[PDB]
Image (spheres, coloured by chain):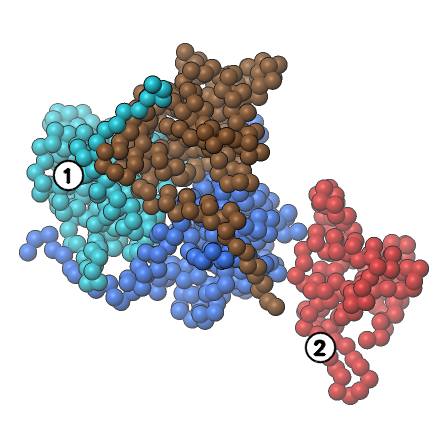
Chain colours: A blue, B cyan, C brown, D red
């Protein structure tokens, strides 16, 4: 009659999503670190190879560089490859680099995993990433492709946004959020110049990783993204 | 004798506040999106009509524009008008636009609600907002005026501040926080210029609204606040 | 054979850390305020007295100024000196200024406390801070030196970083996080200039301290850090 | 059959130079060989016949599906060929480090016999002694 409302049932998809979210919410205290990287060289580098990738049928995005930077951080700061179950003798350290890429789809939140990301080049990752993204979009993923990540990267940047506070998928200890790239005035040396900056948000499980360690891992990533040639070698 | 301490009882007001806060804290995983809007045109527009409002006995603030921008987002992204109770057949979608305005008072946190905000002009909202604010300040609100919101806006900006992390009032799915407006160097086109920026913080319930959707809703709001004429039409 | 994993026991140190963290995570809804202070004068002031401190065997850092600014805020906004236990007649107001300084060590998170911080000068604090830091690093702290804080300051800035989201040590109502200092373009008066900015992150317990109060306390701190002479007098 | 040819390496020289200091800080000596190793892996992948081997019986055409590259060295013990296994999964700095370690092991006779086996292809450097266009003997397998 007035202030109309429509009632709907949670059982179709919402209940399934909530069942997982209601566990993640009290898994651990979570801490997020908000920071920014200067990506001037990254932008220039990706641009330089954009045409080449196109000739090969590969679309470059910045994500493949982020994936490589994360693998490097995971190697330097090995605590990030750990996972924790609830029993006492359950601290697990992985010795491989499997990186999940989150995607928001009509089926909820899916996370395809690139296994052995440590052994792939940038063009190969770009191709695998694009293929997994399409499979996720259409619901064509094999369940075994959504398992085994040591860490996950969540892109919000494709929708715009900065500094969000991603939820750590509960079996892991950290998730890296990626925001948009946009020019901002920065001070470089003695001058105020504009340069593209990438908003980063790192979320970690406080029960295992402390503040200084997480920030150091983030600093590692920031340094590599700002200079792709060192990242590649 | 030394390191003196005074003991007081929680039962006067603190217990009542805590009773509500201790439920909200574990209602859902919450995600906040921190971002900024260029409000150069908004500032100029409000200024232009400041004298007119004064003649009519109306004080303009930026909030009436925020309220209109939120209504527009609520309409474009209808998931934001939903609410969830704990039983399975409890997903409720509202078909009206009732917006709560939070206020910090000596009686705790009050939220007067502007009903049918979708049918009001800017001057009318400014007048209603100011009246509700006074009623809240003095404790003169009728309980029915604090009910029925589809969404709430929390201003911290009147006290200064940026990017806070508002608590979603548990019956709803999102809350919009508003920070201060201040000039910052920005890069506009090819030049570094200063312009007033509004700090925004959007908090949403992860069990229903995903990252991309919340950011899109926020982008909608940012676009409208940056250009009030489109917002009005 | 493939995707190797190593299992380890949580009982050495991790269980102890988790036992505390798993309580703090659901103690209260926590709200963080992210903001920035212009510290141009602070930097210049510390520099001016750097040589003097060195002659006396004292290393100056910015922390002693932060400690004084916090004491001042604690005095102006006395709610910050409170603590809460879980029984009803447990609202405790302290009438002293004991400030904890957090440190990330190989023994987990330690918090030495400077008692009666309100009666110490900057050089004295710098000396006490450095001594406590060394004792914490080596595990030489007396347990009574880790007790009695009214508030805690957490530095992440020594590792780089901005805007983190510190966990309030559960017995208290607020924690102040300190990020790095770095120059950023700012607009000052009518010009775009660069100046060192300090990233601040204030985290508070929503059951006792509201948004406006916490922001006002933060504004107090920001004003004092931007002008050390007023802070000293 | 030998094919004698020449490559313009202006960019290669400039690139190695750029990262020389970095490698030194990490305890890594860069030479051009790590780039040659990567270029060879790429060729082996594009032209897979190069990963084959042949034994003398008829049903002995073997195609490898991995990239193990031998690096020949002339030592006082004769010609040794340490093998970098899974060269396809290593970065330049890592190869430079492995190459230098294998070279030292070969020089001192400290190689484990299993480190001299499994190559799909071998690279022979004569360049360290000067020289152009030599006619290397294909290790028969």
Say which residue label 1 marks. Answer: B112
Between B37 and D129, the one lying in front of the other is: D129
Which quadrant of the view contains residue D115? bottom right
Say which residue label 2 marks. Answer: D63
Q: Which chain carries label 2?
A: D
Q: Is mark 1 on a helix, strand or loop?
A: loop
Residue B146 picture location, percent across and down: 13, 41
Which quadrant of the view contains residue C8? bottom right
In the figure, is residue C87 to the left or right of A113?
A: left
In the figure, is residue C19 to the left or right of A46?
A: left
Residue C68 picture location, percent across and down: 42, 20
Name the residue rendered at 55%, 59% in the picture: C7
Name the residue rendered at 40%, 39% in the picture: C167
Between C202 and B100, the one lying in front of the other is: C202
Name the residue rendered at 54%, 38% in the picture: C105
Residue D33 picture location, percent across and down: 78, 56
Query: Which mark is in front, 1 or 2?
Result: 1
Q: Is residue D23 visible?
A: yes
Residue B154 picture location, percent across and down: 25, 38
């Amino acid at each position: 009659g007035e202030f109309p409302e429509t009632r709907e049932k949670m059982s179709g998809i919402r209940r399934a999503i909530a069942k997982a979210m209601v566990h993640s919410k009290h898994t651990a205290p979570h801490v997020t670190l908000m920071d920014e990287a200067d990506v001037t060289k990254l932008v220039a580098h990706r641009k330089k190879f954009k045409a080449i990738a196109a000739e090969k049928g590969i679309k470059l995005t910045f994500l493949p560089y982020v994936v490589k930077a994360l693998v490097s951080a995971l190697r330097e700061y090995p605590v990030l490859n750990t996972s924790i179950d609830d029993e006492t003798e359950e601290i697990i350290q992985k010795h491989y680099y499997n990186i999940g890429i989150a995607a928001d789809t009509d089926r909820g939140l899916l996370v395809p995993v690139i296994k052995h990301a440590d052994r792939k080049p940038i063009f190969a990752l770009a191709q695998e990433i694009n293929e997994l993204a399409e499979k996720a979009r259409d619901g064509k993923l094999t369940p075994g492709e959504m398992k085994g990540a040591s860490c996950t990267i969540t892109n919000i940047g494709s929708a715009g946004g900065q500094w969000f506070t991603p939820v750590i998928n509960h079996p892991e200890v950290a998730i890296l959020g990626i925001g948009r790239i946009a020019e901002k005035p920065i001070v470089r040396d003695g001058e105020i110049v504009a340069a593209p900056m990438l908003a980063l948000s790192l979320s970690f499980d406080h029960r295992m990783i402390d503040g200084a360690t997480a920030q150091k891992a983030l600093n590692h990533i920031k340094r590599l993204l700002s200079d792709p040639e060192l990242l590649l070698m």
